[PDB]
Image (cartoon, coloured by chain):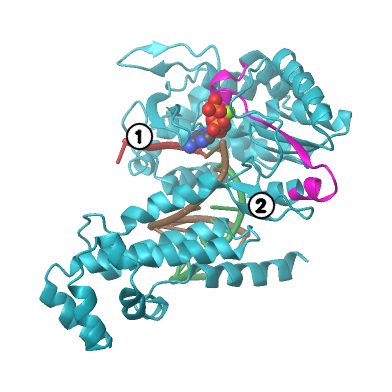
Chain colours: A cyan, B brown, C green, D red
Amino acid sequence: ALLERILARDNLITALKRVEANQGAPGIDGVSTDQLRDYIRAHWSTIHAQLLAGTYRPAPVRRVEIPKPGGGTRQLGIPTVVDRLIQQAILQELTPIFDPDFSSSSFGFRPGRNAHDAVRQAQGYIQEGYRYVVDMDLEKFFDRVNHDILMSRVARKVKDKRVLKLIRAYLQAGVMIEGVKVQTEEGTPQGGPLSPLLANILLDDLDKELEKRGLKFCRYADDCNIYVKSLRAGQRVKQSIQRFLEKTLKLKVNEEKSAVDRPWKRAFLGFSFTPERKARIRLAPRSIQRLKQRIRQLTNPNWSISMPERIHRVNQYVMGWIGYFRLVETPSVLQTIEGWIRRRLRLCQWLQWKRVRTRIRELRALGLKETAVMEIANTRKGAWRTTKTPQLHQALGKTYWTAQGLKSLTQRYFELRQGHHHHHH
DNA sequence: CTCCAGGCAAC
RNA sequence: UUGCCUGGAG
RNA sequence: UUUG
Ligand SMILES: Nc1ncnc2c1ncn2[C@H]1C[C@H](O)[C@@H](COP(=O)(O)OP(=O)(O)OP(=O)(O)O)O1
Ligand SMILES: [Mg+2]
């Protein structure tokens, strides 16, 4: 059955190569992704047998404290590389059982479905007159997930008793803190490969309830938001869904993240909207600030690397960043931050020329007139003040950086948009 | 379509 | 987890 | 370090 289908040779190697590819830090054992291929070849006849025999206890997941963009400490769960390999092999065969019957409005942790699908449907709601959204988020969602309510949802379709025991065992596997197992009464491990599927299984009933109620919503993981026409209707259904998920699913709601405010002052998947009747997608202020704070140090504060290297690092990140923020319909702000990127990249190039004599000889080399070369070189104004002067725009400008190998942000923004909406449409 | 090296994003 | 992007082998 |  399904467990035999999980322990199949080809389902194990594809699951293995994934855990290998991720290059995740090692579990409680300390055995890495690099040692995983050699490791399982040695112990498979055992591991296979003892979990075919229902005598396989998985290792406890390892506690790591990582800071979250909000400022909170995210408690991550890191399983043993074998446990990651197994959980992957469960996930791979559990996806086709559960995924097809998941909501059409469910966009988080599902294959063939991205944040862009969630935002395009969301703009539809404010597009068609539902100009109030009830944005929602759960407190420590993965940490609070209820074992009995989860396995009840899991057991509905999954008839093989062997996998239900196995999945419960992974949920029940305690964690390690300074050399002691701490029993997990609540949660699915953050970073467990299977855990994101289990998360959608629980909130599939939340989608079915909202679908029964006949509401116009978009869910990505716990971050779930319903579109209504009025604030009163939104505030009414804010309490009624809070009552639902608190009683039926047994979860507590994050009131700081949850709100009934207007769509374009709230952030949804790194995007926000415009107050317009045809609400255009814009970058959320956080999303802009995260870019700026990343580009500030790709630009040299006191950083000693090759300038061509810096241009490659600045470009590979920006080009990757815009790959995901190509959805926004405001090119103006993209043109501004691109200029700000160049202006930021001028500061590092200016400071590199430590000597007043080195400034003069390079600027003359760049082609700038000798009149302007001696004026700005002897400036008594600050570094950031000199970067925004007429001279350094002329010598080091859009022409210069583009020739020095810098990839244009706005150029690629259009290149991506043009081809892609030619396809879907 | 499969998989490798690397990157970006949402969680 | 998932989506995407550059490069590579089939 | 820092997982999924
Ligand atoms: N980097 C990550 N690795 C693994 N799981 C993650 C990661 N980021 C987010 N998740 C998962 C687990 C989280 O419980 C879930 C929802 O994200 P989020 O709401 O930001 O965190 P949270 O619900 O655990 O804390 P909070 O109470 O602040 O919402 O998404
Ligand atoms: Mg949450």
- Amino acid at circle 2: His
- Which residue lies under the disc numbered 2? A116
Q: Amino acid at mark 1?
A: Pro
Does residue A139 belong to the magenta stretch?
yes
Residue that appears at 32% across and 34% down: A31
* Labels 2 and 1 in the same subunit: yes
Instruction: Give the label, 2 or 1, closer to the camera.
Output: 2
Residue at image mark 1: A26
Q: Could you tell which of marks 2 and 1 lies nearer the N-terminus? A: 1
Q: Chain of mark 2?
A: A
- Residue segment shown in magenta: A123-146
Q: Where is the N terminus of chain A found, in terms of image quarters?
A: top right
Disc 1 is placed on an element classified as loop
Res A150 seen here: yes
| Residue sitting at x 50%, y 14% | A184
* The one of A377 and A130 positioned closer to us in this rendering: A377
Q: Position of residue A27 (x, y in %)?
A: 37, 30
Please rate how many residues cluster around mark 2, counting C-alpha atoms within 10 Å: few if below 14, some from 14 to 19, many from 20: some
